[PDB]
Image (cartoon, rainbow over all chains, first blue to last red; front, side):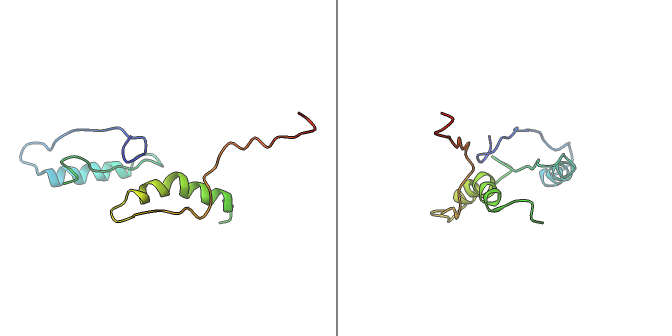
Length: 48
Length: 48
């Protein structure tokens, strides 16, 4: 559970010669095409 | 749209909105103007 709601932690990283910033943007894009009632958030290192 | 009644609106606020708002930066206390749903067993003295 994350911030009181059911969640599933997904780790990962950007490919070589790619920024963390631009890797995260893609994850966000993909995450908007997911089924209804499903959101996301950034935690740990991605939050800061 | 007039699908959710006063009861339904109060539940969704208590279930989905209240807890996250109460843990938000600067929010000291959150007074719910309504009540969260509960399993109401409305008993009958004649049938008992």
